[PDB]
Structure formats: structure tokens, C-alpha cells
Image (spheres, coloured by chain):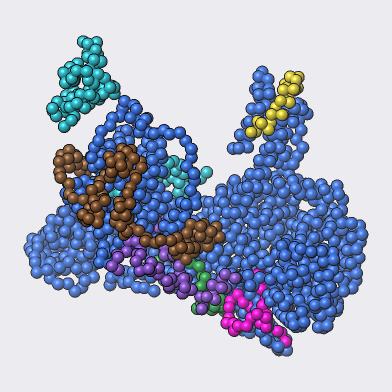
Chain colours: A purple, B brown, C blue, D yellow, E green, F cyan
Amino acid sequence: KSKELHAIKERYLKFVFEWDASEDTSIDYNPLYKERHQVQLLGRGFIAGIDLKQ
Amino acid sequence: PFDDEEPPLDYADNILDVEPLEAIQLELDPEEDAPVLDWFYDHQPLRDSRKYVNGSTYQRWQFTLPMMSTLYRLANQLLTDLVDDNYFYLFDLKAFFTSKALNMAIPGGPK
Amino acid sequence: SYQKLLKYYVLNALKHRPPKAQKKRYLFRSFKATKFFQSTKLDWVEVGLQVCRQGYNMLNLLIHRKNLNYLHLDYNFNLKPVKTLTTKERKKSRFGNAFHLCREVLRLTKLVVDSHVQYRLGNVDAFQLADGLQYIFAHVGQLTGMYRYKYKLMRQIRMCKDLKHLIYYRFNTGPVGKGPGCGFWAAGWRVWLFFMRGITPLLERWLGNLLAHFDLELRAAVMHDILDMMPEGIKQNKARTILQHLSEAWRCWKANIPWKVPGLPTPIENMILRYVKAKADWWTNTAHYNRERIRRGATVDKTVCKKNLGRLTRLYLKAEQERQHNYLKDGPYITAEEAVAVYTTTVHWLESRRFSPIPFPPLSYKHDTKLLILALERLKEAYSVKSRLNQSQREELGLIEQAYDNPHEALSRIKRHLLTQRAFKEVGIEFMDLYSHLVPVYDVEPLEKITDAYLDQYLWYEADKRRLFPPWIKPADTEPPPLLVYKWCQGINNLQDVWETSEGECNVMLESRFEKMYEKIDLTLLNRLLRLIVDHNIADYMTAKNNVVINYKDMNHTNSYGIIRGLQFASFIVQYYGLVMDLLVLGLHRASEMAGPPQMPNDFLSFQDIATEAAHPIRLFCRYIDRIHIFFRFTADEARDLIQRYLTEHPDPNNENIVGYNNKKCWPRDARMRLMKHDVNLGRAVFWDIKNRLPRSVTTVQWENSFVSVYSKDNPNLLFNMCGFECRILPKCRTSYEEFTHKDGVWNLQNEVTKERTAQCFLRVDDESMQRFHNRVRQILMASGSTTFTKIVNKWNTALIGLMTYFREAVVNTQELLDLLVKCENKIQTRIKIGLNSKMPSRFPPVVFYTPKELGGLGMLSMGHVLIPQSDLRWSKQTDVGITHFRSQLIPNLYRYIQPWESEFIDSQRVWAEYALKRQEAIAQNRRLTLEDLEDSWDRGIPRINTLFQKDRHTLAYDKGWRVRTDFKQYQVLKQNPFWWTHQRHDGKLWNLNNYRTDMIQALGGVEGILEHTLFKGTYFPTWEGLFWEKPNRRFTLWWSPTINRANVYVGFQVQLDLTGIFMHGKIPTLKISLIQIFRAHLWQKIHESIVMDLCQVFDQELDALEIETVQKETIHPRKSYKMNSSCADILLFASYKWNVSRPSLLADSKDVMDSTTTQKYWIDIQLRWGDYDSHDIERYARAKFLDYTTDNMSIYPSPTGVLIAIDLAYNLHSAYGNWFPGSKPLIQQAMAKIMKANPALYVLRERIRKGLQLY
Amino acid sequence: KIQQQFSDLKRKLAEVTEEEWLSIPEV
Amino acid sequence: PTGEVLSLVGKLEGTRMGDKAQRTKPQ
Amino acid sequence: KYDILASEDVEGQEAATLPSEGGVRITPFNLQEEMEEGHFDADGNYFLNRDAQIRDSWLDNIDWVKIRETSMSAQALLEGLLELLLPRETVAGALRRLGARSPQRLDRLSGLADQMVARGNLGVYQETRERLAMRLKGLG
């Protein structure tokens, strides 16, 4: 709500080996763009890499 | 691995005749992996078999479906298991090109 | 990591280029074709070993091919120097970045191949091998350090880290815990292969190599062409003659002279002219480019920059000569009827005012001596106390002091010059290099200088007497520009229903410049205008004064159109011409209404009756020296009529009026002017109406330099730029709808009749002012050069004081100015650091800068958040009881110590009302106001109350027009004046920072705390109160040496001083030369010898009563005095019995326990040291050295029982930690007391360091 | 280049005769 | 804790411009 | 320009010879080297001579002073190789025929070839026995 209104107002008015966390994106206010519904792939497809049993 | 004042070991003296340790190899099942059971772990599989590979230059391969299925099952751990490109909606090359041109960042995308 | 990987993926896909077409050529086929190569088939590990050894051999061959043998390249490819490396040797070993990049690439290859060898031998497992390979390919910046020799490699290193993060967090899921067990090296391996694709050509080129005055050029080319077209026989005679003619032509072009050689042939002259034109074009282009670079911020030496300016002077001088030429050709740009119209306007205005023309000064004027004294004082202001006085500079002072000696002859001379002198001498000009714009400055002959100064004073006094100038003309003597802005804002806010827009009324606030005001003043029309208000002879004098030749170096012209603008009475001339322009703009009716009737003239912003106020759109008017600020108020009908008239004259069908509208971009978008069609049209209409009244030939008002802000039902903000202040008035009833606290930049405007807050005026600093200050700091840094650090800090302090006392609340409100101030402060500190040492330090203690000048520091006034570290407020003081440690926080900022302008104005009004009451109650008492009264109003009142008690207050009371005179002083004096707005004599002193200095000393940690970081404790002065300095960068760095040479600020250091016990953390060459001179002639060894001799004498005098057989002077090696790493024995005691010695305790350890042991021999060692600020603790040093040397192998001691007395020469501290036998402790205490009371060599060192510090 | 711009005056330079050459004055 | 000078932006909440500004007494 | 102050002006510049002691380097008591690196002014400044040269990041900062750490006769060789060479073969041909693994014969032949190329001719492995026999006859 407050971040909602603030976004509306804004729109209309050394060797660093590790990346700085300030460069992160996806720090969003809309709950639809944070809690994205996860694809289930009919319960038979799985994401690569992660352990299958998990 | 080695000290800073030792010349490299001679290959003919300490490595030439030493039987190396076993390498990482998965135990392929005799039945469900029959098409690939014989040549899976080779330097250049099927190089000398004119049925499946172009020739010694190793520049083209022709495979049978029972072998492609086995190779596809074995590599599933590295595979996304998606059937569509709708998953990449507004998250693909064109979207990132547009965001760069418009000087905007898609959440979770490049900045 | 995910997003960063995606970024490079997108960049690769986007920056992708088609693979170029070529012809197939293969390197390895070419190699096999030759007879030098052969083919086989080997195991991969064997080839890896061969490549490792081959690379090692090739690197060794490169190193050894210059026949040097002081660097060792081991098998892991670590290039370590053999021995301590000499400066001449530090020049032969310069291989380049390519060498070390190749060496580190071979180190990576060695790591991979050795990992595979470890796997093959059976040392590790296949899984361990894969994990090791992934670790290598991911942790490459921590295993090789390639990135130092190529910075772009951080991209690859970060990419490998990103791949590590992406892979591990899927690998380490479920039962697989987090740890070192992943070996998926297929990604980093690829990343480090595509790197080798790119650098391979580069490194092969390097190994391939290692192994087997543009204008002058153009002139030379032109001369070569001439010689090519020249006969061969005459080459030693005409070639120099032709070059001489070309040089003469260039000199004439620089001086704008018509170079011509009749003897030179016509084609030769034409070629020389073409070369001169090309050189002039190149010079103009180069000068423009260099000026743009300097203005942007490019750094160059002051000499070449001065050359560039002088080049720009010649271009402007040529342009001004051309302008005078066009005026001489085109005649008077003003038409005759325009001339008679303006003349009729002024005569009508002045007869309306019943003005009495200023007469020629009679012989016996009551105040003529007073005005002459004022003029001489004003001239003396230019000549500060200095030793740079040339023949003309000292001639001017000789003349003004002679005038002081005999005022009457001087006054007669002035009057004679007025009556007769019409022809004058050439006026020299230079320019102040304000990086935004060049300001001319004019140098007038000293006799003419005195004449013009007296005329300026006299005319200003008479005009102030006769009220020639109505109150709207600014700047006035009664009011500084910051109060100008406040009075303007209040006058706007106090108008009748000024903020009401229900009916549709619109307020318009206009500001302009009167473009080219000084330049476009016709001297004949000027004479005609001056003849009314002044005597005709005086007018003839001043008008003849501006018809004078102007010279610079070699180029000179006469000025027929412009006003000299550097004359002393140019102030009066400009202020009168501006009044005539005001008559043109306002019209006689409205001008009379504002000025009020002559017998009862109105003040700045007030009318006789409110009906008179609301009798015209123009409510307020205020002309600065050349700026104009007009405030209109229109009804709906008036606004629409004006819009209709404008559109009739200038139709706007497509609504194109919204394109060239100037706006105040510094404010937020909702706070700027809102460009609605009606408001834009109204602003354009009012500007066009104002422009039409002024004839274009006399002066012009240009839209792109003007700003017209309209307040209506659409725009709730009123904006204007006045005297450097950026103001925005926002009415409370209009779009405020919010309770407000007290904000520094916000002014709470209130209605003078109902005392209700109707509006707020937000304040900001002009972009022009911020840029001017930034350019001032840039001048300070760039013109520093060889100047002392004290002078640089003084100039910075002057600039900061001027800015912070002019823009008091505005700087607080302006965030950009705060950032600029902090940046400039850091730049000044960095320049001081670089002067101190070339290497940029870390955490330089600010105590060096912010310490007061009288206390040895620089005295930097602070405008930033500086946190003094708590480790910087620790000091130690040593007395006979021992060493006592104490502690004492944010450094105070200026803006807290200057009263805000608003509070200053309200206090001034109240205090001056109080003074009026006290003055009337006192002349009721028939006495004079004393110091006891008004004492509560001492530093109050914008005309400071203190000005009532000066000595020259009667004399100053005759100094009229001093503020405009000070403003015009920048046009005559080569020194930029930060205080162009105020005068110390008239306005008093408006700021007080003595409390700032006291809080400064308190914040740095007190006088003691400041002195701890200094070498004061080395001076062995009992107190600080009674000392004085002798007015220096060498003295400065030596004074602050103990806190500058500390290991913290400079690391990777502690090179030992020769024949000296001093560690220099960092190459501080100034400290090094100071320390060489201060320890000359083996001073450290003499110290050690004399202290050992003194202890030996003390102990001989106390031999028997301490049960001693004898005292042995142990053989001291000559370099033992400065031998820190180990030690030896200095004094050996033989007891002839067995002493009972105690556990090693400090010198002040009055409570000591017996060691339950006995000994016969007792060694005494002395360790001298130069303690810095961090490590001056003599007790810790003594205990550590005693416990280290006793348990050391290179320190041979005769007995395990002994003492080690450590003496800190830097802080005159001492402590002994070793064992003690009966009587040894109190006697040793007495001994050290006596040795630091009267040791000849310690006294020699103290006296020497006092001489070096110049502190007596 | 520079000589490419100066070529016209250079070609016109050879037009002058030798009687005006030793008469060239110095500054 | 470096000795570098920090911007006053956002650090003026607890201070006014006029506080700690004093007035001198006649000599 | 300002007169660079002499090293005698500061005085007390003992001619130290030791380069270091206990790891830490020993700076010279004389400013001759420092003046050569960067000249002083008349008031003790340090205008550094602008080091215009290649960049050596290792050299400009050496890890804070880092860690401070018989031949046989030519005719004899030719005779040996010829005796060691089979008919109608080059030296490379002999190496190939004997490398399908007498190992010691192969070792000796390859060694002789390596010495021979070390002599200064690189065309060793591209010469048949006839050419080298003729060469031996020419030198004999």
C-alpha cells in the first residue's frame, strides 16, 4: 500500500570479488511479483540440478 | 600440489608404469541402458564405427532412437524438463533487449 | 549471481558480430610442413609436464638474458628477488605487465598439471581431483593474482564466482550438505579457455618483441613549401627573412596590427598571409578548446593556462576593437527620436521630483575634506599590507599618502582636473578567470584614480542627499542583499489578497538582465542625460573619461561606445542609466506612484494608499545594478486582454509557445512552474509588453536569459532568482494542507497586519553561485603549486566563510551544495596529503588539518560530518609518579555557529527599535548612550550596534553608495572579493567564530590532546602557555611527524634510517630530511654513549653501598645504539657477593615480589627508540624488549638477571622492566631523574629538536 | 594536408622573379 | 573509521542552524 | 626553477653501506638517491621526476619488499650413427623402425641425433644414410 503509492509518485513525478548486494533486483512490492506460482509440470516434470526427492 | 623448490617429476620415472586409480563412472544397468552400455565412457565413442559416426575426423554423428532415449534419460538431472517457451514469457532475449533499450530493469533480470 | 550471469549473456547475444570472411590458414599445419617439428602420440600428463618445464625454461631465459642474477623464479612460478633490491637494479628488472601475466598463466597451467600428476601417482582420488580442478578454476584470484597485471580479468573472476554460486546451490541440496565436495569444473574451465583465446596474440607479440607543437609543425610545413618553391642559391638569406616576416605577421595579428612588408614579393606576402590565417585559426580553436576544458574542470599548469587566458584576452580585445569600429561606421545605434524621447522622459521625471541639479564642488565645501579622506581610504583598501609594490604600485601609495598629507592641494588639483582635463592616459586591462565567464578589470592612472574616487564619493553623497535615486534602485547602503530578498518576499506576501485566485486573478513575477547594459550606453546620449542632474563641467569630465584608449600588453583601442566600467564613478553612471531605464519600463505615472510624492517619499516596497498600490498591474519593482525584478498582478480581464494583444502581434496557432520557456530545473517537478497554455501565454504576453517599452537600440531584454513565473489557479508556486537566492513562495491556503515544523531553508512569511502565516518561502542556492564556488576551489587547488599548506587552507577558509555567511539558510536547504562542499573539503585534504607524501594514505588523522594555526595546525573550518576516532583523543603525560593516560565525538560544523538570516533580521528590527527607545530616553536624560547600555544588544542589528561606537562613525556617515562601490570593486581590483556584499566598517561584523575555535580545540581533545600528536613532548617544554612561533611546510610536517609516520597510516614499511634508530613508515622525504638534520653527526650513538656514561658514573658513586665489586663498560658495538632487532649488554656489575634479585618488574612497580634466586653479575641494557603516536608507550616497549631479548639467540647476555631501560626520545619517556636487587630500584629511579634533568647529550638532542621545530 | 591547402600559393610562389628575392627585407 | 569528510545530508535532524551560536561581550 | 638543496645542506649524511638489517631495509643517510628519484626545492619539497616508462605493477610494489628470498668427435658421431643406421633409411627412419616397443640401440641412435642437431644443423632427421655417408667421405 505505502510502497504502492510511493512507486506511483516516483513514476509520475578496491578489488570487489563478490557482487554488491545493492545491485539486486526483484525487491518488489506487488505480492503477485514476489510469491510467483511455481510450475508443477503436471507433477511429472522437475527442475534441473536440485535433488529429485526434495 | 607440489613444493616451490622441487623440479617437476619425470613422467617416465613416477607415472609411466603406475596403474592409475579408477575414474568416476556410473554403473550403467545392463538392460535399460543396453544401447549405450558398450561405448558410453570412451575418449571418442563410435569413432571407428562407420554406421554411427562420419569417420576418423569425427565431424558428424547419426544415432538411433533407442540410443537417443537412453542418452536423454541419463542427462535428465541437467535438463529443465520444460515442454514450452511460455515459461520465458517477458524473460527472454527480446524482453531483455527492450529493457536495456528503455533503460529499465525487469525484476530478476539484468540491470 | 543469476542476474549478473544474465547480463553477460544478453551482452554477448547483443554485441555479437558476424565471423569475418577469410582464407583458411592453419598454424600447426604450417609448423608440420617445416623440418623443425615432428609428430608423436603421448599421454596428456606427460605433455603437461613438458609444457610446464618449457614455460619455466623460457621465463628463466628471459630473466637471464640481460645477465642479471638477483631475481629467482622458482618452479611454482613465484618471482622473488634474491636480495634487497637497488634503485638502479629497480630499473633493469622492469619487464612489463605482459611478463607477469604470462608467468601467472603458466602458474595456472602448473596447478592443473600438478593436480593431474597427484591424481596419477595415487595421492588423491578421482573425486578429489575433480574437486581440486573446480576449486582452481573458481578460486583463481586467490591462487594466482593475475588481476593485478590486467584489470579486465575481474570480469572473468566474478563470472567464475557467479558460476560457483549457481552450481553449488543446486549441487548442495537434500542429503548433500554444504562443504567442499563438488567437482563440476565444466564451467570455470570453459571461462578460462575463452580468456586464453584473446590474450594469446597479445602474449605472442610481447614474446616476439622481447625475443629475436602542431602550430610549429604547420609553420615548418609552410616554410618547407616556400623553400620548395624557392631558389636553391638564396637559402641562408631569405629563409630567415621570410620566417622573420611570418613572425612579424603573427605578432601583428596577435596585436591586431596590419603587418605589411613592401619589399617582400606579392606571392610571398600572400603565402605568408595564408600561413598567418591558418596559425590564427589554429590558435583560436586551441584557445577555445583549452578554455572549455578548464571550465569543465581539466587540470593544467597555471603558466600555460595564463597563456591561454591572455590569448582569449587578445580575441576579446580584437572583438571590442571591431565593435567600436562598427559603432564608428554605423554611427549611434539609438535613433534621434528615441534619444529625444528618453531625454524628455527623464526631464519630466526629474521636474516631477523637483530635483536640484548637483553643482560643481565649491572651494570651501563643508565636507570636501571628509569625502577626500573617504576616497583615499577606499583606494587604500585595494593595497593590502604586502611587499609586492612595483614602481606604479608604490607610486599610487606615494600619491594617496601625499594627498593625506595636504588635502587642500589635492582638492584643488581634483577641481582643476574636473574643470580642464579632458584627455587622459591609456587604461590597462586584465581579466579575472572565473571559469564560468571572464570579467574585465581596468587599471586607471593613480592621479586619475584619485580624481575619479573623489568624484564618486562626492556624487554619491550629493545624490543620497538630494534623493536622486528612488528606493527601488538597489543595492542600497541601508540593507544587504540577503535582506533585499527577505524584504522582497515580505512585500509580495503583504499585498492585498495577493494569494487569492477564486476570481481567476494571476500574479506574474518577472526577472531579466538588461542585456549588454554597460556596452550599449551611447556616450553622447550619456552626456546629455548627465547634464541635467550634475553640472555640465562634471558631466563633460566623466563622459570624456570613458572616451579613453584601453591597452593590454601591446594591443590597444579607444572606447567610444561602451563605458569603461572600471572607473570609480562608473557606479554612479550605471545607477543613473538604470534609473532612466526604470522610467522607460514603469512609465512616469507608475514610477511616481511607487516613489511617492517628493516631500514624503515611500520606502522600498510601500505605497501611500492601497488604492495606489492596486492602481496598475505592476505592484512591485526592484532594479539591481542591471537585473530587474517586476511583480505583476492581473485580474482575469487584464490578463486576457494582454494575452489577446500578444497573440495578435505574435499568433501561436500550433501551441508552440511551450518550447522556449525557461524553468527552474533545480526544484522538483511538482514545485516548478507548470506549463499550462493560459499561464505560458500570459508569461509570454507580459514579457513582450515589457520588452516593447524598451527601445532595442538602448538596451534589450532577452527571453532566454529571463524567467517569467506565473501564479494562477494552475500554478500554486511563485518562483524567482534574486541576488543569488533561489526562492519559491508557496501560500498556505494553496496546496500546502500540511502542518509544518521549523525547517532551516524555509522562511515563514506572515501578513504584517494580521500576523498570520500565509505563505512559506523555500530557499536555495543559485546554480551560478554553486558553480562560482566550485571554480574558486578549483582555482585554489590548481594555483596552489609551490604554496605553503597554510596559504591553501587560508584560501579555502576564506571561500567557505564567504559562502556560508552569504547563503546562511540556503546552503542548509541546498543538498547539492552540501555534497559539493564535502567534495571540495576532501579534495583540499587530498592535495595536502599528496604534498605531504606522494602515496595516498589511509585514515589520515584529521587533527593535522583542524588544529588551530596558533596551536601548530592548519585551522581548517569544517562543513562536513567528520567523526574523530576515539583512538585519537588519547594522550599520556609523564611525571615522577609515572606515565598517566587520559581520554576526552563529532567535529563542529560552521553552519551551527552562524545565526540564520531570518533570526538575524527579526533580532535586528527588535534591537534597533530598542535602540530608538533608549536613544530618546537618553537625550531626555541629556547624556550619550554608553557601553553599559545596549550591552545586551552588542552583536545584534544588521547595521551592527558596534558601528555606533566606532571612531570614524562621523566620517563613515558621509560615505554614501558604499555597497554599490564595493560591488564595483571587483571591476577594478585584481583580487576576487568574497565579501563584495558587506563592509566591515559600515555593517560591522556579521559573524563570530571564536566559540567555534574553542569548541574546535575541545573536540580535537583539548590543547594537550592536540599536542600529543605533535612533537611538543619532545621539546621537553614544561608547559604550552608561554610559547610563541616565528612567522613553513617543513616545520609543519616535522611538527606533526609523530602522528604522520605511524604504521597505521602507511603499511608495508618501516625502512630503517641510517645510523639512526628511527623507523619511517612510508617514504616521507620531508620528514626524512628533517630527521637526518636533527640526528646529524651520529647523534643517536652519542645519546647512547652519554647515557651509558652517566649511568656508569651514578653507579660508581653508589658502588659500595649497593654491595658492588666493580662496574664494567661492556664492549658496545658502534652500531649497537641503533640495533633494534637484537641487543647486547651495556653496563656490567660485579657484586663480589651474591645479590638477591626480584622478578622482572616495571620501574614504577613499587610492589615487587622476590624471584627466590641469587646472582653475582647484573647486566644493564639501554634501548633507545623513536615512539610514534600509536607506540610511544615506553612501559610496554621496555617490557616487550626485555622479555624478547632475554629469550633471544642473537642477543647474548652475560647473566639471565639484569635490567633493560628503554628511553623514548620522542616523548621523553622511560621505563625499566628487568630484575632488581636491593637499592637498585630507588637508585635507578633517582638516576633516570638526574639523567633527564641534566644529561649533556639528551639536552643537546632536546635543544636540536627545538631548533628544528623553531619553537622557543 | 597542410601542403595540400598551401599548394595554390606554393605554385603561385614560383611565378615571382629573382629580382625581388635578394631585396626581401628583414625584421 | 577513516578521516574522510562526510556529507551533512540527513545528519541535521538533531541540530538547528542557530544553536551553539554565541555573542561576544564588549572589550 | 627552485635550487635543489644540496645533500651537504642537511649534513649528517653518514655513508652507510649496509643494505638491510633484520629484514627491514636501511635507508641511506644521504639524500643523493632521493634527489635522483625526486629533486628537492629550496624549501624542502619533493617534486618527483615524472616516471614516464612502461607499467610493471609487480615492480612498482614488490609485495612490500616481498619476502627478500664429453662430446664425441664429429667424425666419431657420424661413424656411430652410420653404423647404427640400417640400409636405405634416414635417422628418423631408424628411430621409427626401432621405436615399435633394441631399446638401447634406439636410445643411442636418438642420443647421437640429438647431439648432432645440437652441433648446429637442424636437417639431421631429414637425411638418408647415403647423404651422411657422402658427407663423411667428404670430411675424410
Of the pair C870 and C668, the residue shown nearer to us: C668
Where does residue C202 sit, x and y in percent of width and height?
41, 40
Q: Residue at x 78, y 56 (%)?
A: C519
Where does residue C108 sit, x and y in percent of width and height?
30, 47
Q: Quadrant of the N terminus of chain C?
A: bottom left
Kindly give the residue lying farthest to the left in the view shown: C1137
Q: Residue at x 73, y 26 (%)?
A: D12
Query: Which range is magenta?
Result: C725-753
Q: Quadrant of residue B56?
A: top left
Of the pair C568 and C705, the residue shown nearer to us: C705
Q: Quadrant of the C terminus of chain C?
A: bottom left
Q: Residue at x 30, y 36 (%)?
A: C58
Left or right, C727 with reference to B74: right
In the rendered image, the vertical position of residue C399 relative to residue C578, given as above or below: above
Left or right, B108 with reference to C565: left
Left or right, C950 with reference to F48: right
In the rendered image, the vertical position of residue C16 relative to residue C363, given as above or below: above
Where does residue C1123 sit, x and y in percent of width and height?
25, 52
In the rendered image, the vertical position of residue C765 relative to residue F103, given as above or below: below
